[PDB]
């Protein structure tokens, strides 16, 4: 039952949990009808053959009909009593059951349903293999068991065994058995209805008569009408009795008829509570069935006075309140009594409103009495109770505080709070606060003795109470509460229940709050909490509590702490108040030394997860993974034994330490930082010494029975790391390497010989000096007359013939001309540089229209010191050019200047440094003279643009010229963008816009060629870094530009977007998405590349321990970018263009994704499901990008997010409110929403991919899907699925091919080497925010729905089955040994020695090839 998945209705497999949450698109029905003296003749339900596959779909259809009828009758409520609601519900339940081939007594076209059901059972093969009416009895039993829990999930008033629902919802058995004949069931329904009508109408008539004061004539007329209808009812009853006698004489369906005749024959013939935490039974106190194993009841609620005309009822409430006052007066005898009154006030409110969550033995009778009283005295009953509570809580609160004389409405009997005392909170949170307050009281009384005799001053005086506090929390004893169970289990139950309410409020109600404020229901309060960010219980407790009632040390509720001690030891991670010791009292009540090594260990600062008198070997085992024997260790026919494990451990140790050194020296209170950094430096140095000793012992053992040395192995590792990072295929030939790349490889880590030990030594020295440096942190000459030799330079302007880029790497124009007319040389060069500097300053002052983003006036951008813009950079590059001129470094210049360089070298390096310092002093003196003759506004020589000189490690010739090129390109692009937007904003292009766009297109074409040459040269020189990131950080001019799109090298870029990021502005057309039903002119205009599997994971472009998947780095963000930069501060018209682009982008992404996973080789159920999940993941990524909850900031996504903020309200509106507005825009329309439109566009692309002669898949018929999880979680799931799939592929390939085992081991080792670090990063990030939220996590994202102890337990229960393709799409067969699978301890035992025996010769030849490469490089000259 309900096992069918992906049904013809459109959706499936959502059932088996939250079963009554069924829409029309779940059964294989012909028509999706919502089902909008027979009393049900008008419309009961009309939903109910050749299309149905199995009986499960028909059962789902009947489940849908019952749910629709249940919702319809609940929302209708024809009767105003609201007490006998479920009686009509079960009557409709019996009626719908009788429709399925029963006593169909409805006059009319009753044969249509009968014939349809007959063909239905015919298709089901009622004449089954096992012998005919067994199907009807079996399905009726299945019907009676199943649909009762679905139809009854709407109404929750009462049912007269279980209550608080129409029978039950989780009891799993029916309450009442309605085996009565439908012929007389209608008679029983009507006569029962007429009884209640008679008692109501006679009372209404009496009320009208006494309220009146010629109404006597009306009274008589009603009396005769009542007599007339009573006579009709008696006559009808007599006729029905005559029919009964006729049928009885006639006697004198098999089972149903026999039962009916059998029934016809029978008719003819107080105490202190202890915080009860258990579920509520029939007649015992306890939490409700929906509240089973939830927050318990305090003693106050169970010992209330209630447990022990409108004017009459309100006086009764006053008397109840007045009696309740002495109960709290004697039970509590200041602040303790006031809170008790407030909770009792709120508990009374929820009891009156009908939202009690405890339901004692007398609660059901009291609720029924309240329903009858308000039914007799007075939209909806629940709204009436809420209105009564709001308008009478004013007097009830005063009544409870010594209510004897009710005045019209401090000095009264209490001074708790004001008159209203607003406490409109759900009862679950109030019970949670009361339990936490009671726990805080117990914690404070236990912690007070500890602090008083453990104040850093211990043999036995302090540890005894520390053990008592540890014993008090670590069991179900010592403190009151939790109902005889550990505190951690109840806290976990509270966290699970709070998360469930957060999920239910977030998904069940699309828009609950902001309907008028809040709607004052259960979902609105949780919606408000989610908006605030208090989605975790710890955040809620911290904000609401005073933070001082417990601990006496300001112990936060958000600082989670974990303890291992509890025969078996289980790690328990809980908040700070739930701890074995007080906050900061870990290893402190023992009164020991600070232990700074472990002191920084608990802080998670520079963690090193390594644990390195014969002294044969050292373990150096990794934490968590346990060292095991090789299992193939042999002494005969084996080169080595018990050394492969050390080799793998040393290799993994080397990789992790190198990654840690790179991350710690490139990334980064400072005194304690470098203390722990110094401890880490000492630790790795000890590890390196131990590894050196073991590797030496390994070498001697190998020589005893030719292995490569430590330097040879380290040189191979750098080469291998380089190949995997960039080559990514481990190609045999490596001759295709540039000279710049080869020099970088020979200079970075390894020289021609092997110097790996020097590599580690220099890395340690570099780390130490960075640690040391981080912790540690006259001129009077005047010769103005001598000005002759050079003239103003040929600048790129016309004021009254401009130097062009002659483009080795490139040659800028200003470098081509310098004030070098003179070219003993010290004075000449000093005068030349000074003359050039003042001349450059003069042109930048007046000619400030080339490299300064400002008008002809300028200086209104401008430097903070008041100097001209773009003056520091030009001066610095001029000095760099002069430095390389005199020094003679690598320069891309022809023979014009080479003669001068040879002359300078022939005429003549501490002297050069002294010369450079002299020129710096001369430039400083010249700048001061310029300041002197410029009225001496302020004192400044070199602090304008940084006191220190340019000492970049990178070459200052090619990089600086590349910086100059991009700055000129970026400034000119902004000017051209301004000119276009001022001249082409007001349709076709025939005026002053074609010339501007055409000039821009030529300009982009020229700079594209220069960009390709410069980018290629930079990549050959610097392969580790990129070009776009360098330009963006140095120059904030072109934050809006993207070199990938503007200088895109594809062939379709010159057709669909030929104008380079301003096609939309220069075209002035309108975009549109041609759907499947639209015109034949489909939207096949895109720059999407064909997806490839060669791409790998990388952590670049992320604002730690998170890696971007290959799928996310290949999504099409090309079509959005011209439209994004088109609109600026425009939300009205940009809504249409953004939506149309998103549909086009989503359609293309699904089309290419399906072609990737079905590229003529994988046409199977698993391939379809994998493509289905990839399309879903892309949809979630697009949703998170639009919602602004994205982690990675690429070139496209960064500006898309920035412009999305700008398109919405400006800085007056808060960024969080802008984020909410974007979320609301994506969710709702402000026909269908953008979420469904994008999903339908993705479906339409899949139809095109399928039609390119295949059937449609099953896992794309889902009209709606569940809300996305956090982004990191989906990336982790994709990583696990790819890890398990690739692991299975390589292992099965290795087992069969192990005479080709060398290749299998090589691919296995190369693929598994980075995955271990990726697993460590993923696991560290998962543990960091495992149960965090917006105000607890480092990022403002919701993670309260995870609630997992560790990442390995989370992969369980999600990747432990088949590829469903809708919710779960990961499968694995190594769920247990996941951390060990990253290593090679257990899963690679049988093929352990073979891989090293193959890798040894591989290492030897690779080092031999890498040794001969520099020899061929040197011999080529």
Image: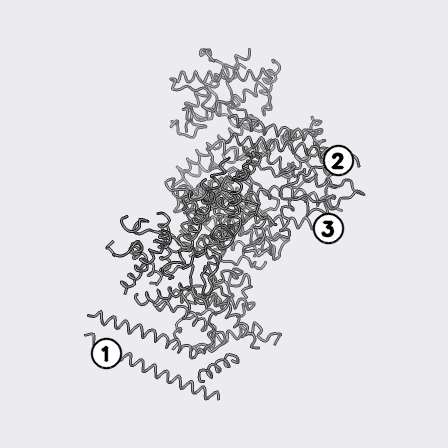
Q: CA distance from mark 2 to mark 3?
A: 28 Å
How packed mark 1 is, by other alpha carbons closer than 10 Å (few <14, some 14-19, many 20 or more), is few
Q: Is residue 728 above or below residue 782?
A: below
Residue 307 x %, y %: 38, 61
Residue 871 x %, y %: 46, 24
Label disc, if present, on residue 707 of the rendered structure? 2
- Quadrant of residue 1129 in the image? top left
* Scheme by which the image is coloured: one colour
- Residue 679 shows in the view: yes
Secondary structure at numbered mark 3: helix
Secondary structure at numbered mark 1: helix
Q: Is residue 1396 left or right of residue 126?
A: right
Q: Nearer the viewer, mark 3 or mark 1?
A: 1
- Of 804 and 349, nearer the camera is 349
Secondary structure at numbered mark 2: loop
Q: Is residue 871 above or below residue 1329?
A: above
Say if mark 3 contacts mark 1, CB within 8 Å: no
Q: Earlier in the sequence, mark 3 or mark 1?
A: 1
Residue 197 x %, y %: 33, 73
Q: Nearer the viewer, mark 1 or mark 2?
A: 1
Q: Is residue 1418 left or right of residue 1232?
A: right
- Of 916 and 59, nearer the camera is 59
Residue 269 x %, y %: 45, 85
For the view shown, which residue lies furthest in the left direction? Answer: 214
Say if mark 1 contacts mark 2, CB within 8 Å: no
- Of 1251 and 171, nearer the camera is 171
Label disc, if present, on residue 1296 of the rendered structure? 3
């Amino acid at each position: 039952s309900e096992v069918q998945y992906y049904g013809s209705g459109g959706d499936g497999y959502y059932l088996r949990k939250n079963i009554c949450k069924i829409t029309v698109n779940h059964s294989d029905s012909g028509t999706n009808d919502p089902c909008d003296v027979p009393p049900r003749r008008q419309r009961m339900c009309i939903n109910n053959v050749d299309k149905i596959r199995d009986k499960h779909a028909f059962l789902a259809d009947v489940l849908l009909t019952a749910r629709n009828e249940g919702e319809r009758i609940v929302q209708n409520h024809p009767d105003t009593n609201s007490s006998n609601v479920c009686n009509a519900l079960e009557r409709s339940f019996a009626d719908i059951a009788d429709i399925i081939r029963g006593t169909d007594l409805w006059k009319g076209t009753n044969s249509n349903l009968e014939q349809n059901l007959k063909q239905m059972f015919a298709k089901i093969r009622e004449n089954d293999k096992v012998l005919y009416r067994k199907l009807r009895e079996d399905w009726w039993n299945a019907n009676r068991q199943k649909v009762w829990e679905v139809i009854t999930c709407g109404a929750r008033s009462n049912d007269l065994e279980l209550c608080r629902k129409c029978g039950h919802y989780e009891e799993k058995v029916p309450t009442k058995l309605d085996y009565v004949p439908q012929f007389l069931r209608w008679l029983t329904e009507w006569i029962e209805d007429f009884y209640r009508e008679k008692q109501n109408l006679i009372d209404d008539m009496e009320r009208h008569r006494e309220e009146c004061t010629s109404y006597c004539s009306t009274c008589k007329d009603k009396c005769k009408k009542y007599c007339e209808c009573v006579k009709k009812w008696k006559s009808e009853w007599e006729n029905q009795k005559n029919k009964y006698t006729e049928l009885y004489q006639q006697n004198k369906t098999s089972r149903y008829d026999d039962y009916v005749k059998d029934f016809f024959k029978k008719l003819e013939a107080k105490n202190n509570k202890n915080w009860i935490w258990k579920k509520s039974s029939g007649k015992e106190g306890g939490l409700q069935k929906e509240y089973a194993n939830t927050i318990g009841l305090p003693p106050r609620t169970q010992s209330l006075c209630l447990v022990v005309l409108l004017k009459e009822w309100i006086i009764a409430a006053f008397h109840e309140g007045k009696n309740l006052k002495p109960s709290h007066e004697k039970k509590n005898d200041g602040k303790k009594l006031c809170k008790a009154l407030e909770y009792s006030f709120a508990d009374y409110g929820d009891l009156i409103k009908g939202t009690s969550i405890w339901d004692n033995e007398y609660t059901k009778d009291l609720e029924l009495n309240l329903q009858k009283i308000f039914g007799k005295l007075f939209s909806s009953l629940d709204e009436l109770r809420e209105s009564w509570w709001n308008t009478n809580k004013k007097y009830i609160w005063l009544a409870m505080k010594h209510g004897a004389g009710m005045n019209s409405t401090t000095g009264s009997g209490s001074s708790c709070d004001d008159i209203p005392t607003i406490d409109l909170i759900p009862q679950y949170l109030r019970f949670l606060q009361e339990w936490v307050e009671h726990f805080c009281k117990q914690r404070q009384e236990k912690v007070k003795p500890v602090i008083e005799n453990c104040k850093s001053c211990c043999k036995t005086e302090c540890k005894n109470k520390c053990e008592v506090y540890k014993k008090f929390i670590e069991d179900c004893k010592g403190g009151d509460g939790t109902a005889g169970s550990s505190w951690v289990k109840r806290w976990d139950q509270i966290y699970k229940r709070y998360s469930k309410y957060i999920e239910d409020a977030k998904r069940n109600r699309k828009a609950g709050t902001k309907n008028c404020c809040v709607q004052s229901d259960i979902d609105s309060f949780f919606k408000h909490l989610i908006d605030i960010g208090l989605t975790t219980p710890s955040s809620y407790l911290s904000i609401v509590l005073d933070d001082n009632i417990c601990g006496a040390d300001k112990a936060p509720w958000t600082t989670y702490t974990t303890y291992t001690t509890t025969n078996t030891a289980v790690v328990v991670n809980v908040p700070s108040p739930l701890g074995n010791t007080p906050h900061g009292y870990k290893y402190a009540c023992q009164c020991k030394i600070p232990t700074n090594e472990e002191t920084c260990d608990d802080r998670k600062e520079y963690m090193n997860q390594w644990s390195c008198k014969n002294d044969n070997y050292e373990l150096c085992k990794y934490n968590g993974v346990d060292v095991k024997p090789t299992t193939v260790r042999s002494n005969s026919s084996k080169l080595d034994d018990k050394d492969v494990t050390f080799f793998n451990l040393f290799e993994q140790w080397n990789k992790e330490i190198q990654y840690q050194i790179e991350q710690y020296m490139t990334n980064t209170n400072c005194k304690e930082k470098c203390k722990c950094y110094s401890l880490w430096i000492e630790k790795i140095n000890d590890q390196w010494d131990k590894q050196k000793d073991n590797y030496n012992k390994f070498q001697r053992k190998q020589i005893y029975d030719k292995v490569v040395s430590l330097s040879n192995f380290l040189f191979f590792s750098c080469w291998e790391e380089y190949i995997q990072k960039y080559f990514n295929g481990d190609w045999s030939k490596i001759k295709n390497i540039g000279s710049d790349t080869f020099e970088f490889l020979i200079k970075k880590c390894g020289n021609d010989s092997g110097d790996g030990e020097t590599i580690f030594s220099e890395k340690l020295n570099n780390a130490e000096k960075k640690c040391k440096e981080n912790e540690s942190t006259s001129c009077d000459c005047s010769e103005p007359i001598y000005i002759r030799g050079c003239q103003p330079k040929i600048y790129d302007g016309k004021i009254f013939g401009e130097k062009q880029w002659i483009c080795g790497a490139c040659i800028p124009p200003r470098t081509q001309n310098l004030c070098v007319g003179e070219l003993s040389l010290k004075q000449k060069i000093k005068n030349a540089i000074q003359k050039e500097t003042e001349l450059l300053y003069e042109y930048h002052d007046k000619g400030t229209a080339i490299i300064s983003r400002n008008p002809m006036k300028g200086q209104k951008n401008n430097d903070s010191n008041g100097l001209p813009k773009g003056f520091c950079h030009a001066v610095q590059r001029s000095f760099i050019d002069y430095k390389n001129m005199i020094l003679g470094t690598s320069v891309n210049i022809y023979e014009y200047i080479g003669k001068l360089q040879e002359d300078i070298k022939k005429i003549i390096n501490a002297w050069w440094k002294g010369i450079e310092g002299e020129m710096w002093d001369a430039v400083r003196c010249a700048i001061t003279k310029i300041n002197k003759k410029q009225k001496k506004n302020g004192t400044f020589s070199i602090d304008e643009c940084g006191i220190f000189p340019p000492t970049g490690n990178d070459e200052d010739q090619s990089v600086s010229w590349f910086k100059e090129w991009s700055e000129q390109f970026c400034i000119e692009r902004l000017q051209y963008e301004k000119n276009i937007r001022d001249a082409c904003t007001n349709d076709k292009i025939q005026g002053d816009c074609k010339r501007k766009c055409e000039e821009y297109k030529k300009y982009i074409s020229e700079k594209k060629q220069e960009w390709d040459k410069q980018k290629t040269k930079y990549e050959n020189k610097y392969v580790g870094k990129s070009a776009s990131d360098l330009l963006k950080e140095n120059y904030p001019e072109c934050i809006s530009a993207n070199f990938d799109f503007i200088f895109n090298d594809n062939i379709e870029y010159k057709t669909y977007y030929p104008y380079g990021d301003y096609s939309s502005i220069c075209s002035c057309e309108q975009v549109k998405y041609y759907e499947y039903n639209n015109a034949e002119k489909k939207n096949n205009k895109s720059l999407c590349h064909e997806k490839g599997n060669d791409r790998t994971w990388s952590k670049k472009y992320i604002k730690e321990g998170v890696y971007v998947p290959p799928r996310r780095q290949q999504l099409c963000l090309y079509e959005l970018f011209p439209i994004i930069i088109k609109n600026k501060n425009d939300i009205t018209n940009a809504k249409k263009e953004l939506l149309e682009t998103l549909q086009i982008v989503a359609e293309r992404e699904a089309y290419y994704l399906w072609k990737q996973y079905h590229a003529h080789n994988d046409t199977t159920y698993l391939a379809h499901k994998k493509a289905c999940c990839a399309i879903r993941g892309s949809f979630y990524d697009l949703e998170d990008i639009i919602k602004g909850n994205d982690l990675v900031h690429d070139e496209y996504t960064k500006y898309i997010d920035s412009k999305l903020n700008e398109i919405f309200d400006s800085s007056n509106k808060n960024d969080i409110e802008t984020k909410r507005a974007r979320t609301d825009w994506w969710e709702n329309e402000a026909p269908k929403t953008i979420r469904q439109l994008v999903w339908d566009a993705m479906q339409s692309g899949v139809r095109k991919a399928i039609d390119e002669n295949e059937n449609f898949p099953p896992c794309m018929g889902v009209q709606h899907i569940g809300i996305a999880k956090p982004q990191f979680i989906r990336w982790l799931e994709e990583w696990t699925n790819e890890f398990c799939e690739k692991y299975t592929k390589y292992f099965e390939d290795m087992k069969s091919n192990c005479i080709e085992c060398k290749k299998a081991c090589a691919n296995y080792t190369n693929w598994l080497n980075p995955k271990r670090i990726e697993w460590n990063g993923m696991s560290n990030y998962y543990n960091k925010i495992y149960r965090k939220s917006n105000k607890e996590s480092e990022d403002g994202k919701d993670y309260s729905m995870i609630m997992e102890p560790t990442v390995i337990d989370y992969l369980n229960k999600r990747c432990n089955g088949e590829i469903n393709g809708n919710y779960i799409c990961c499968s694995c067969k190594n769920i247990g040994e996941n951390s060990t699978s990253g290593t090679v301890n257990k899963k690679l035992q049988k093929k352990e020695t073979q891989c090293e025996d193959n890798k040894g010769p591989l290492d030897l030849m690779n080092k031999v090839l890498n040794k001969m490469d520099p020899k061929y490089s040197e011999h080529k000259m």
